[PDB]
Image: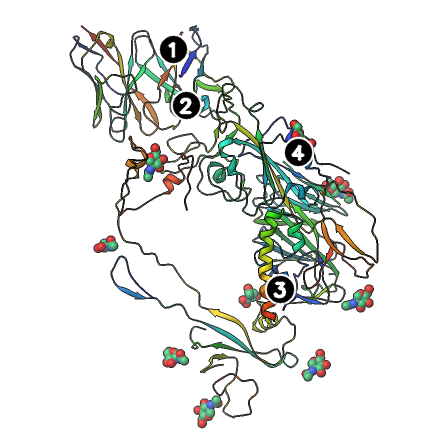
Amino acid sequence: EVQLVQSGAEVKKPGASVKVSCKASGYTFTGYYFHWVRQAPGQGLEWMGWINPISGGTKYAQKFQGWVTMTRATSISTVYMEVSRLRSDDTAVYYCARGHTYNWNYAYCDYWGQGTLVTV
Amino acid sequence: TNLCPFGEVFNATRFASVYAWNRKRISNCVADYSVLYNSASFSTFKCYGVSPTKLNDLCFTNVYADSFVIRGDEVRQIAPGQTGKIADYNYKLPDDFTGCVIAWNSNNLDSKVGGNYNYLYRLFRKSNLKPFERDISTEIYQAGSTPCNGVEGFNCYFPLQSYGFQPTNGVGYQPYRVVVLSFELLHAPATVCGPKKSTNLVKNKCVNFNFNGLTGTGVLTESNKKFLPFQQFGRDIADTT
Amino acid sequence: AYTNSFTRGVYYPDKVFRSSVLHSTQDLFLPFFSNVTWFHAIHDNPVLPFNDGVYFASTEKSNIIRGWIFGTTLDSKTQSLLIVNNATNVVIKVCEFQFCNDPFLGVNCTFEYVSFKNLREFVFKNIDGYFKIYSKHTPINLVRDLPQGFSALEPLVDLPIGINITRFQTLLALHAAYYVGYLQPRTFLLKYNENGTITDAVDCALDPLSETKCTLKSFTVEKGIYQTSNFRVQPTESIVRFPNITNLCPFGEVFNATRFASVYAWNRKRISNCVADYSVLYNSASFSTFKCY
Amino acid sequence: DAVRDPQTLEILDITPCSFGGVSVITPGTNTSNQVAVLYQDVNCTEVNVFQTRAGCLIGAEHVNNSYECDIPIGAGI
Amino acid sequence: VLTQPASVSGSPGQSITISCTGTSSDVGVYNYVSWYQQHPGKAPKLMIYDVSNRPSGVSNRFSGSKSGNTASLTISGLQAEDEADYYCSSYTSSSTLVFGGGTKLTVL
Amino acid sequence: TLVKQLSSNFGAISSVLNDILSRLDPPEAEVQIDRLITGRLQSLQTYV
Ligand SMILES: *[C@@H]1O[C@H](CO)[C@@H](O)[C@H](O)[C@H]1NC(C)=O
Ligand SMILES: *[C@@H]1O[C@H](CO)[C@@H](O)[C@H](O)[C@H]1NC(C)=O
Ligand SMILES: *[C@@H]1O[C@H](CO)[C@@H](O)[C@H](O)[C@H]1NC(C)=O
Ligand SMILES: *[C@@H]1O[C@H](CO)[C@@H](O)[C@H](O)[C@H]1NC(C)=O
Ligand SMILES: *[C@@H]1O[C@H](CO)[C@@H](O)[C@H](O)[C@H]1NC(C)=O
Ligand SMILES: *[C@@H]1O[C@H](CO)[C@@H](O)[C@H](O)[C@H]1NC(C)=O
Ligand SMILES: *[C@@H]1O[C@H](CO)[C@@H](O)[C@H](O)[C@H]1NC(C)=O
C-alpha cells in the first residue's frame, strides 16, 4: 500500500526558509509524480507544483515561481519542498501527494501524506 | 603474448544500462574461451556462425565487447530478427550476426531491496533502431500539436524508464547481466589468436598446413611472387589460395 | 572551375595479390572522365559534402595541404576525425574537437595514433563505420591541372572510428590547388600485369563500347555486333487506390472488454468494413507476446 | 491483365512498360573506337537515326548504294 | 479558481448537493472533475475522479456530475460521518491543476 | 566456365568447403555442404 510520511511541524520567522520532506514507500518511487498542496488554517487547498523523480523535472504554481524549490533523492525515496522568503500568509499545512506520471491531467493528487504544519 | 582483459569486463563491478550500453574494443591477444565455456557459471551461452570449441582454436582480426542489464523474460530478444521493447528501442543485433551472446543470473549482485532505480530502457520512438544505433537522447518526443518545451507533459514523457528489480520477484522478473561478443573479419591479419602453439615449417614435402586458421594440404616451396606489403594472400582462378 | 578527371581515382579494391588477369569488381571509384571541382591555394577551404565517399587530389611543390577533418558539424558537438601531417608526423585523432571558424595551420576521445612536382591522390571512404584511406604519391611535371595518365592507389589505413560522416573540410598551411570528386558504386575491369600492378582499367558505365568491353571481359573487341544489355523504360510516379470509406473497427470493446469467456466456450466476433490501425497496438508495448505467421 | 478501379467502376488495361535488347555495331577497336547502337524491337521514339525492322539504329549513316554484306543487322540490312 | 458554496447543511438520511462552477478553460469540455473529502483534522482523500467515477471503498451514495462549465457532487442518505470539507478540483488550460474554495458540509 | 563455377556459394556461407568445416559443427556444416553439393553436381551435369 502507498505510504507517504512527512517531516514534523515547523515554526519560522518572516524572511526565513523552510524545507519539508516527504518519504515515500509501497510502490515504484520513480514511476509517479509528487504534488505539493498547501492549506492555510481554515482555508481551501492551494496547488504548489509537481516534481518528476526521473531527472528532477518540475513545474510550479505561477504565484510561487522564484521562491519554491522541489527536489528528490531517488536513493532514499524522498521528495523535498523548500519555500524561501516566508511571510505570515505562508502559515499552512503542507501536504505532499502522490499522483500520475503523465503531466497534463486532472485530479493529480491521489494519495496524500499526513501534512506538515508550518507556522510563520 | 598479451591476453584479453576479460577479467575487468565480466568481473566488472559496475554496468551501464541498456540504452547507454558500453563498448570496449579489444584486440591483439591470446584468447582462451574455454575458461568461460567450462566455467559452467552461465545460465545461457549461445552464438551463431561458430561453435565455441571451434572458435577457441581460430584467429580473428577484430572483436568488440558490449554489456548491459536486461530482464529475464526478455533475454531471448538479444538475437537476430527479434521483436519487443529492447529489440525496437534499446538494442538490435544485425541479422547476419557473427558474435557470441552470454547471460547469467545476477540477482545476488545487481538487485537490491526496495527496487534498484539505476538501470533504464528506452520506450518510444518514431522509428526502429538501426544496427548498433545508440540513442542517449532524453529529448521529449512530441506526438501532438501543442509545443513540448522540454517539460514532461500531456505528450510523450521521457523515452527512459527504470526497472524495479525487487529481489522478491520471479525468475523472469530478475536482472540477468549480458555480454555480447562480436567477431568480424577484414583484410587485416588476425590479432586475437587462440592458445595454439606453432611448429617448424618443412619445405618441398607434402604437408598439412595451418597459417592463421587457413588450412589445406600441399607442398610449400619458396617463391618469387612479389606480394605488396599490405597483401597476405594470393589467389587462383578457383578462388583457392 | 572544373576539370577532367580522365582515368584517375583507381585504388586497389582489396589486399589480395593478383597478376596477369582482368578482374571485374564493384566498388566506390571515381567515374572516368567525370568533373571534379577545382579549388585554388594561390593569391579556399570551404566545407564540402562527403556523400558516400570522396576523392581528393592535390598538386604540391611545398606541402601546403596538411590535413583533413571529417564529421557532420565539425564544431565540438560530435566526434570528428582529424588527420594532420605536421612536418614528418602523421597524427590521427577522433576527439570532439573545437575547430576554428576558419580552420588552418600556420607555418571525449576514442582514438589516437602517431607515425607542381608531387601529385598526391587520396581516397576517403566509410563502410559500416570503417574509415578507409588510400593514397598514392607520384612525381609530376605539371602546374596547370591534373596530369593525364593511369596510376593505382594503395591502402594505408583502416580506422574503426564509427563516426557518422556527411561533411568534410581541408587544412591548408599558411605562411597548391586541389580537387574534390565523389565516388560512385561503378563496376571496373581492372588490368593487373605480370607483377600484380594495376596498369589499366575500364569504367563499365562510361559508354557503349566500354559496356561491350566489360561484357566480353576484354580490353579488345573483335569486329561484329554485340548484345550487351537490356533496356527498360523506368516508371515516373505512383498511383494509390483504396475504396473511400471511414468506419473504424471496435477493437476497443474487444481488447478492453470487461468480461471474457472461458476457452471451451471461446467467443467469436466477426468484424468487417473498417479502417484498421494495428500500429496503435503494435507500438503499445503493453503485450508480453505478439507473434503471427 | 486488367483491373476494376475500386473507387470508380471502370476497367483499366495494364500494359507493361516498353523494353528491349541493345546491340552495339562495331568495327574492331584495332581500327576505330567509333560505334553504332541498335535498340532492338522498338520505335525511334522512347529512345543520324535510321528506323529498320530490326529496331532503331543510331549512329550509322544511311546510304543508297548496295554492297556485299559485312556486319549483318537484319531484314536485308 | 472554481467556485463552491462555503456551507451546505442537511439532516441524516436526506440528499444534499454541492455545486462547483468554473469556466471553459477548466470545467467546460474538454475537462474532467475530481472531488476530495477532507474529514476534520485529516488529509484530503479522493472521492470522485473523471466527473462521476468512484475509487474503491467510496459508497454509491456519493455521485458526481458535470454539465457544461459546472459540476455537482450529490450525497444521498446523508450520515454524520459525512461532516467534512469537500473540494472540487479540475484540469485548467491544458497546463495546471486548480481547486474550488471548499464546501463545509454539516450534518444536523 | 566449369572451373569458375566452384567459386559460387549457391547460397552457402562460403564457396570454400574447408571454411565451412573449420567453423561449424557437423549438424550445421551438413546443411551448408548440401547447398554446395547441389550447385556443383548441377554444374558437372551441364558440362557433360
Ligand atoms: C561537367 O561540367 C561541364 C562544364 O564545364 C558541363 O558541360 C558537363 O555537362 C559536366 N558533366 C557532368 C557529367 O557533370
Ligand atoms: C606535431 O604534432 C604533435 C602533437 O600531435 C607534436 O608532438 C609534435 O612535436 C609536432 N611536430 C613535430 C615536427 O614534432
Ligand atoms: C616487373 O618488375 C621488374 C623490375 O623489378 C621489371 O624488369 C619487369 O619488366 C616488370 N614487369 C612488368 C609486367 O612490367
Ligand atoms: C469514392 O468517392 C465518392 C465520393 O466522392 C463516392 O461516390 C464513391 O461511392 C466512393 N467509392 C467507394 C468504393 O466508397
Ligand atoms: C592491330 O594493332 C596493332 C598495334 O597495336 C598492330 O601491330 C597490328 O598490325 C594491328 N592489326 C590489324 C589486323 O589491324
Ligand atoms: C513508330 O511510331 C509512328 C507514330 O509516331 C508510327 O507511324 C510507326 O508505324 C511506328 N513504327 C514502329 C515500327 O513501331
Ligand atoms: C536516295 O536517293 C533518293 C533520290 O532518288 C533520295 O530521296 C533518298 O533520300 C536517298 N536515300 C539515301 C539512303 O541516301
Residue at disc 2, secondary structure = loop
- Give the CA distance from mark 2 to mark 4: 48 Å
Residue placed under numbered mark 2 in the picture: A33
Q: Do tags 4 and 3 sit on the same chain?
A: no
Residue A14 against residue B9 in the figure, above or below: above
Please tell me how crowded label 2 is: few (under 14), some (14-19), or many (20+) other residues with Cα within 10 Å. Answer: many
- Give the CA distance from mark 2 to mark 3: 67 Å
Circle nearer the viewer, 1 or 4: 4
State if disc 4 and disc 1 touch (CB < 8 Å): no
State if disc 3 and disc 4 touch (CB < 8 Å): no
Give the chain letter at badge 4. B
- Give the CA distance from mark 2 to mark 1: 17 Å
Quarter-of-image position of residue C182: bottom right
Q: Do tags 2 and 3 sit on the same chain?
A: no
Quarter-of-image position of residue B219: bottom right
Closer to the camera in the image, C86 or D71: D71
Circle nearer the viewer, 4 or 3: 4
E55 sits left or right of F8 in the view: left
Residue at disc 3, secondary structure = helix
- Give the CA distance from mark 1 to mark 4: 57 Å
Circle nearer the viewer, 3 or 1: 3
Residue placed under numbered mark 3 in the picture: F5
Residue B67 against residue D28 in the figure, above or below: above
| Residue at point 45%, 43% (across, down) | B127
Q: Quadrant of the N terminus of chain A?
A: top left
Amino acid type at circle 3 is Gln
State if disc 4 and disc 2 touch (CB < 8 Å): no
Whether residue D13 is visible here, answered yes or no, is yes
Amino acid type at circle 2 is Tyr
Where ligand 1 lies, by image quadrant? bottom right
Identify the disc placed on residue A114: 1
Give the chain letter at badge 2. A
